[PDB]
Length: 44
Image 1 (tube, rainbow, N blue to C red):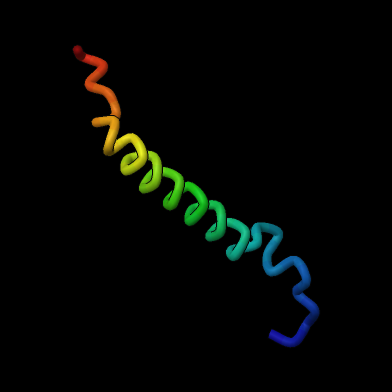
Image 2 (cartoon, rainbow, N blue to C red):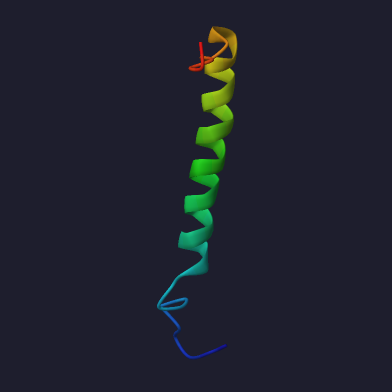
């Protein structure tokens, strides 16, 4: 692809991909920091 895609795609994949990792890390971190807390157990 030589044409200045600029718009890597009207839906830039890297932007889409970055979003997933941000959330990926967020959920993993969420679980651990909450891990020590034992998070919850709402049911209780």
